[PDB]
Amino acid sequence: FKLPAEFITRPHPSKDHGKETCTAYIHPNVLSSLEINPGSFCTVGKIGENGILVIARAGDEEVHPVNVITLSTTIRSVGNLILGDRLELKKAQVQPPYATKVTVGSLQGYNILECMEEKVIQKLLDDSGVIMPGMIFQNLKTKAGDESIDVVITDASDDSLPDVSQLDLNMDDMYGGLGSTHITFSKETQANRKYNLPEPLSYAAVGGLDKEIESLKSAIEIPLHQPTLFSSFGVSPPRGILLHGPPGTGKTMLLRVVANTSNAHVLTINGPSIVSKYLGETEAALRDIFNEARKYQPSIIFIDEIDSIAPNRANDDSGEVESRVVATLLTLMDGMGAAGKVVVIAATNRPNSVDPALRRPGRFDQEVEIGIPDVDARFDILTKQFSRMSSDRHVLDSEAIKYIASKTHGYVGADLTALCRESVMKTIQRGLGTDANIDKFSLKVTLKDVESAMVDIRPSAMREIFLEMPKVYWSDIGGQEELKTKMKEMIQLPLEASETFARLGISAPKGVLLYGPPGCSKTLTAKALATESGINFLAVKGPEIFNKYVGESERAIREIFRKARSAAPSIIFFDEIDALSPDRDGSSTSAANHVLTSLLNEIDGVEELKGVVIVAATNRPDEIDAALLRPGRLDRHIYVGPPDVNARLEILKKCTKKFNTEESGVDLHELADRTEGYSGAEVVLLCQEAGLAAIMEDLDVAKVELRHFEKAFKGIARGITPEMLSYYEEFALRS
Amino acid sequence: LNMDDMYGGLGSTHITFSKETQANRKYNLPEPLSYAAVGGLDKEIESLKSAIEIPLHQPTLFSSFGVSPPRGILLHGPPGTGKTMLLRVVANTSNAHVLTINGPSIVSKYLGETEAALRDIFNEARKYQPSIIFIDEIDSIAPNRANDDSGEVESRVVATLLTLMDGMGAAGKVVVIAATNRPNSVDPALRRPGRFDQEVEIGIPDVDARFDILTKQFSRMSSDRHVLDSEAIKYIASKTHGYVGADLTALCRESVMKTIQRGLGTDANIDKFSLKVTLKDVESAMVDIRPSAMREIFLEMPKVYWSDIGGQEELKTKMKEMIQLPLEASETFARLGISAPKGVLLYGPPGCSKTLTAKALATESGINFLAVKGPE
Ligand SMILES: Nc1ncnc2c1ncn2[C@@H]1O[C@H](COP(=O)(O)OP(=O)(O)OP(=O)(O)O)[C@@H](O)[C@H]1O
Ligand SMILES: Nc1ncnc2c1ncn2[C@@H]1O[C@H](COP(=O)(O)OP(=O)(O)OP(=O)(O)O)[C@@H](O)[C@H]1O
Ligand SMILES: Nc1ncnc2c1ncn2[C@@H]1O[C@H](COP(=O)(O)OP(=O)(O)O)[C@@H](O)[C@H]1O
Ligand SMILES: Nc1ncnc2c1ncn2[C@@H]1O[C@H](COP(=O)(O)OP(=O)(O)O)[C@@H](O)[C@H]1O
C-alpha cells in the first residue's frame, strides 16, 4: 500500500568497496511491490531515453528512506544521471548474451600505463554487474608516483537483439586473481560516437566570460565548501544568485555546466508546470521542494524564467500568480537555516520585468552580469568549437578564425553555433548536389560556404541596422577633423573610463546635441559616430515613436529604451527630434507633452542611465522646450556647418571616382569653388544630375563636357537663404 | 470489397488485361497529392526536399560532427499561397510518421489536459524513430508576448514547446514544420536560430510561376474538357499580375460556372463537351471577380495608343528620358554613381494633359503600371 511514484538518486556513502555498482539501497516494501527478487536486476526509468540502465539490486538495513535511491558515482557518470532527477522502476529485461572484446581508452592521459598497469582487469571486474560501455573509477593507488588516471571504455564491438537497450549491457565471465578475451588495452579511443552517448558538459566548454564564470564559481563555492568559516563572522551567507543577460548568451548552458561539474545535490524547476488551478497545491509543492532541498545540507537550487514565474506586481496584478508566490518564496528562502549551504540560481531575460522585491540587497545582493561577447570572446568560442569537432573534419587557420570573428561582430555564441550548423548542412547539400555521393571527408569545411552562411542567416535581432559592414565607412566621407576629435573623445569616455567614473564620482553627463542647417551633414555625422563606435546602432526617428493610439508612443519609448539598456553600452539617436520638441509653439497635443515629460524623466530624472548615451538631432533648435535646453543634458552644441573647401573637394573626388578625372575636363577645384553656397545634399545631387545631363546625348556615355555642367548649375537652385543661416548663428550667440 | 476466386497454382474472371486508364472517378475516391500538382516553386520545393531529407534519411552523417541536427523548420507566406498543400503533399509522399494537429481543438479550459495531450503526442513522436510533427496557425496558439497579455494559454506553451524540442534525443530523426500567416505575429522565442534557424518563405507567384500553375491545372483536367493554347495561357498569366494559385483556381471555377450557365441559357442543355472551355468566359470572369488585392488603391487604369495623345514634344522628350534611363542604364548608373533619383514632380494647370503623360506611359512602357487617386 506504499504506492511509490518517483525516486531520487544519491551517491553511495562510506565509499570503500562494498557494491559500488549495484547498491540500489531500496526499502524492502518496494522490492516486494515489484514482485522481483532483491538479488536480481533493477531498472531506473529516468523518464525517456529507453535502455533504463538495468543494474543489479541489493537490500538496505531498514533506515534508508524509501524515496531516495543510490546509483553510485560510477553509474552517475556513465549515464549522466545528475542529482535530484526523477526515476521509475520496472521489471528487468533479458539477461545479457556475452561480452566480446571491451577496449580501454585511457581518458585525458598519454597512455603508456604498463608500468602502473598491475593487471587492471581484476580491478575493473572485481565487481558485480558492471556495464561494459561504462566504467569510471578513481585512480585509487597505482604503484609509486600517485597521480590520477581515468579510463574510457565506451567503445564496443558487439550487438544485442533488443533495440530498447541503449548501452547494450554485457555479462562478465573471465578469470582474475587479487586470460581475458584477446587483451583489452588498445589505442587511446575517445567516447564512441556510434551509440550517441550524452557527452557531459565540461567546465572549459564555455568561455569568453572567464572572469564572470570564475567570480560566479567562487561566490557559489565559498559558502558550500566553507560554511563554518563564514558562519564565524555571524553575518550568514545569502542564498540568492541572479543571472541575467541578452538572449542566446548561453546562461542555461553554464547552469547545466555548473550542475554537471558539481557533485552536490542540484534542483531545478520545469517551468510553469508547478503552477496549477488549485491555490494550495502550488504552495504545497513549493514547500515539499524546499523541504527536500534543506533536508540534505549540500543542495543547489536552479530557477529559470523567474520573470514569468514571479512577474512585477505593480506592472500587472492579474491574479492567481501574484505577489503571494513572491512572498512565499521569499519566506522560504529567508530562513531555511542559520548558516547552512544553499545557493539559488535564477536566470531571467529581462531584469526590469522581475519583481523589484526579488531584486533587493537583503535577498539577492549578489548579481552576475552577462553581456554580448566581443571580438576576443567570439574568437575563443569559434576556436573551442573547432577543437570540439576536431581538425579531422575541417581545416581553418587562426587568421581565418579571426577574420570570421571580425566579420560577425554582432553575433552571439548561439548565433555562432547556428552558423556552424548551417555551414555544415550547406556543405553537405553542395557535396550531394555536385560531387555525386562522394565521401564527406574529402570536401570537409571551406571558407565560401561559411561566408554564404553568415550572409544568408542575418543577425538574430531582425531589426534594420547599418551594422557598418555593408554601409558607408570613414574613408568614403570627407569632413572636418575638428568635430571628429571631439566625438572620438566624447564616446571613448564611457566605453574606456567606466571604472574612472565610478572611482572619481564625476560620471558622465550623457548629453550631446547636434544642430545643423537643412541640407548639411547631420545624419552623416550620426552615421560617422555609429561607424567609429563599432557598437549596435538603433535607427530611431521622431515621428516613428508617434502613433494614432493614445499611449502607444509611451509603450514604444519604453520598448526602445529597455532594448538599448539590454543592448550593451551603446548610443541612442533620434533623427528628427524637432517633431516632438516644441509644445508651446503650434499648440501641441497632450500626447506630445506626455512624451516630452517621459523623455525628460528618462534622460536625467530620478534615475541615471550609465550604459546608453543619448544623442539628439533637430532641424531647428530654437523652438525646443526650455526644460530640455538645460545644462547637464544635451549641453554640448556643435555648429557642424556646411563642408569647407577640402571636404567639398574630397566629396567631389569620391563622386568623381566612379567617373574618370582625366577626361572630365575639370580640376576638381573649380567646381567646388563655384558650388560654395549649396547645401551638402545639393552638392551630392549636383554630380548625379550633371551625369544625367552628360548621358542625355546617347544614353551610355564615357565623356562629360563643360556645357553639361553649366546646364546642371543653371537648372538647379540652392534653396538656402541667408536668413536661416543668420537665425542659426543667432542661436549660437544666444547660447 | 469482394471475395477472390482463382483456379490455378503457384482462369481468372473473364480476362483482366484491358487498357491502362487512371483511377476510376465514379467512386470519387480521394487521390494522394504529389509534386506534379505543385508548380512554379522549383527552387523552394527543392529546398524543402533537402531540409526534410537531410535529417530523416541520413542523420548519422550530420551527427558525427556533434553539433546536433536542426529540428525546427519555419514556413510562412501570404494567405492562399498554397503552403498547406505543400504540407499535405510532403505528408502523402513521406513514408514516415506524421503528427498533424487540429490546433484550437486540443486547447481547453483545463491547463493540465493540454499539457497531458502535449506529453502523449511528443512521447509518441520520440518513441518511434521515424516521425514528423506538423503545426499550423503558429501565431494564434502562440501569440507574441509583447503584443498582449492574453492569459490562460500564453507563453507557457511556448516555454514547454522549447523544452520539448531542445532535448528530444542526441541524434534522432525528428523535425517540426510551422506554418504561419505572418511571421511578425509569431512569438520571437520560437523565431530563434537555436529553434527555427531554417526559414522557408513562399512568396507571391510571378508571371512564370502563374503560367506554370495554369499549365499544370489544365494538364490535370486534360484536353478532353477544354481547348487552350500556349499563347492564351501566357496572356492569362500576364493579365493576372497579382493573382495567386488559389485565385487562379477560383478564376477557373467561376469561368466553369459561367460557361455552364451560358450553355444552359442559350444552347438549351447541349452536350457538356461540345461547349467545353473558351477564352471569353475566362475574360469575363477575371473582369467581374475584382483583382486579388482587396480594396486596392493602386488600380489598373486603361491604356490608349500614341496617335490618340496630343501634347508638347518637350514633355514627351522628358518622358522618354525618364523611362529610357532606368531600364537600360542600370550598369551605367552603377559604374558612374549616378544611381536613380526616382523623384519627378508634375505640376500644372488642371485638366490639360497632367495625367495624359502617365496614361501614355502606362500604354507604351508595358511594365506593370499602378495608379492611386489621391483622396482615395
Ligand atoms: N558561447 C557559446 N559557445 C558555444 N556554443 C554556444 C554558445 N552559446 C550558445 N551555444 C550553443 O547554443 C545552445 C543554446 O544555449 P542555451 O540553451 O544555454 O541558451 P540561453 O542563451 O541560455 O537561452 P534559452 O534559455 O532560451 O535556451 C547551447 O546548448 C550551445 O549548443
Ligand atoms: N501551385 C499550385 N497549383 C495549384 N493550385 C494551387 C497552387 N498553389 C495554391 N493553389 C490553390 O490554393 C489553394 C490552397 O490554399 P492553402 O490553404 O493550401 O494555402 P496557404 O498559403 O497554405 O494558406 P492558408 O493559411 O489559408 O492555409 C487551393 O485552392 C489550391 O488549388
Ligand atoms: N557626402 C555625402 N555623401 C552622401 N550623402 C550625404 C553626404 N552628406 C550628406 N548626405 C546625406 O544628406 C542627409 C543630410 O540630412 P540633413 O539635411 O542634415 O537633415 P536636416 O535637414 O534634418 O538637417 C543625410 O541623410 C545623408 O544621407
Ligand atoms: N485624345 C483624347 N480624347 C479624348 N479624351 C482624352 C484624350 N486624351 C486625354 N483624354 C482624357 O483627358 C483626361 C486627362 O486627365 P488630366 O486632365 O491630365 O488629369 P488632371 O485633371 O489631374 O489634370 C483623361 O482622363 C482622358 O480620359
Image (tube, coloured by chain):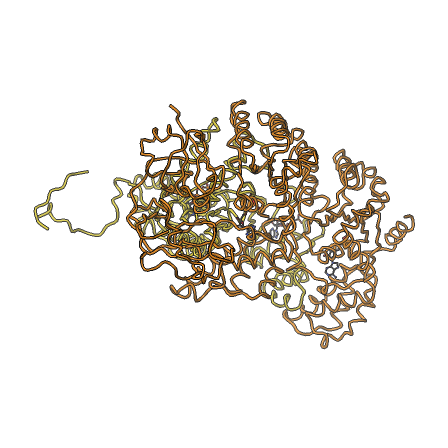
Image hue for chain B: yellow
Residue A281 seen in render? yes
- Spot the residue most to the bottom: A662
Residue A520 point in image, percent of width and height: 79, 57
- Tell whether B28 sits left or right of A636: left
Q: Quadrant of the C terminus of chain B?
A: top right
Residue A725 point in image, percent of width and height: 86, 54
Residue B281 seen in render? no
- The one of B163 and A160 positioned closer to us in this rendering: A160
Chain shown in orange = A
Residue B332 point in image, percent of width and height: 63, 68
Residue B259 point in image, percent of width and height: 37, 43
- The one of A451 and A161 positioned closer to us in this rendering: A161
Establish if B203 lies above or below A10.
below
Q: Identify the image quadrant of residue B257.
A: top left
Establish if A548 lies above or below B298.
above
